[PDB]
Length: 169
Ligand SMILES: Nc1ncnc2c1ncn2[C@@H]1O[C@H](COP(=O)(O)OP(=O)(O)OC[C@H]2O[C@H](O)[C@H](O)[C@@H]2O)[C@@H](O)[C@H]1O
Image 1 (cartoon, rainbow, N blue to C red):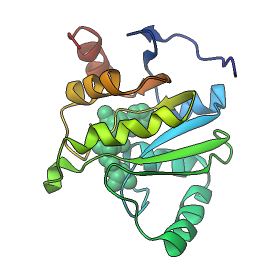
Image 2 (image 1 turned 90 degrees about the horizontal axis):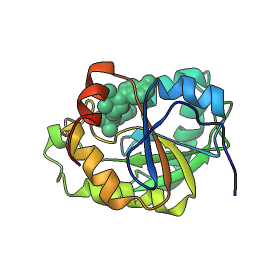
Image 3 (image 1 turned 120 degrees about the vertical axis):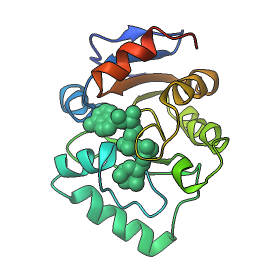
């Protein structure tokens, strides 16, 4: 059931682990079965996790995503799709957290994290915690209280990581 080479993760719960790391570098090191992208409904991979993952695939993720949207239309807020992980992972699970900065319901963050339960092991970011404007501690708490499968969270920002791991969740 895949034993992966995740290294240097702090344990949060039975099934959630966390590390101060760039998700791109973790994916290159581990080559997991599933890397999660913090996507938008249009799969336009501009910045943050999505832009960094896409750049590391030499834009192949974006080209594949454009074909996905042309065939299927936008994802739902809280929804997901499974696409290739290209050189980074077997699969990329593109998951859309709510864009709280655009008035989308923060409750949809739970629906977003539920997608993780369809996969035994994931390398993932904190959904909605960047430009989508959700409180990062809240995103972590929802993750812990929603995901039952094994999730390795990569937190790029050191100061944020230090705050998250010293917080009650
Ligand atoms: N390379 C990285 N590795 C790990 N964590 C990262 C990295 N880059 C950012 N983070 C953290 O990952 C967390 C999420 O930040 P975000 O990636 O903005 O995702 P969202 O769900 O809020 O916004 C999605 C939009 O952003 C994109 O443009 C998409 O195309 C969408 O339009 C934050 O804590 C970041 O510090």
